[PDB]
Image 1 (cartoon, helix red, strand yellow):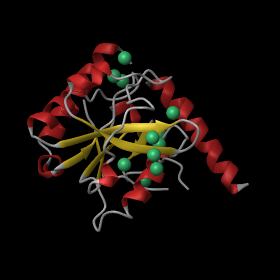
Image 2 (image 1 turned 45 degrees about the vertical axis):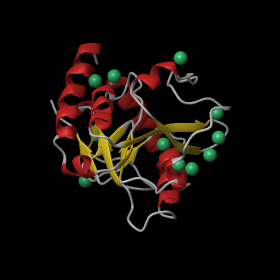
Image 3 (image 1 turned 180 degrees about the horizontal axis):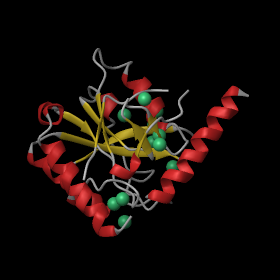
Length: 195
Ligand SMILES: [Mg+2]
Ligand SMILES: [Mg+2]
Ligand SMILES: [Mg+2]
Ligand SMILES: [Mg+2]
Ligand SMILES: [Mg+2]
Ligand SMILES: [Mg+2]
Ligand SMILES: [Mg+2]
Ligand code: NI
Ligand code: NI
Ligand code: NI
Ligand code: NI
């Protein structure tokens, strides 16, 4: 019952948030602001092994950050989701240009296909820094995802491979910042956002 009330609150907020999620140019504008903030960010600059998402249209565009990741010689991993469940791995990509050749999911997001053998981040040391996607975030680092809980489960696996947990950095539109995100689940270290 209390569980259902939480679910209801999340569902309502998701609706409210997805409504808010803007022009194409404003999305690009705000993505450019965040990329600069990211490139200037201490945790990002120091990170050696990085997980980053490939942007949907209701998400901060990560294209510029991906270019920079490879320029800084970081080891770059992207999501590969198993849609049958809440399982995801982070799989290694070797250049920004590789992304353009990948097959795409029903979300129109690139990820390596079923027969494509990939280095999984947890097989080779884990991650220093994970960029956290989501529908909404509050100033306490509470995250509202799409409902499937992939990132929550992934973070718990990271604990089994690393003495120190990966730093988690959320990238948000101004429109994605909420007063209170209803919660059960796992906070992000920092939410970046502004005009
Ligand atoms: Mg927007
Ligand atoms: Mg976008
Ligand atoms: Mg699948
Ligand atoms: Mg997993
Ligand atoms: Mg393709
Ligand atoms: Mg697999
Ligand atoms: Mg609010
Ligand atoms: Ni992995
Ligand atoms: Ni797997
Ligand atoms: Ni998730
Ligand atoms: Ni509060």
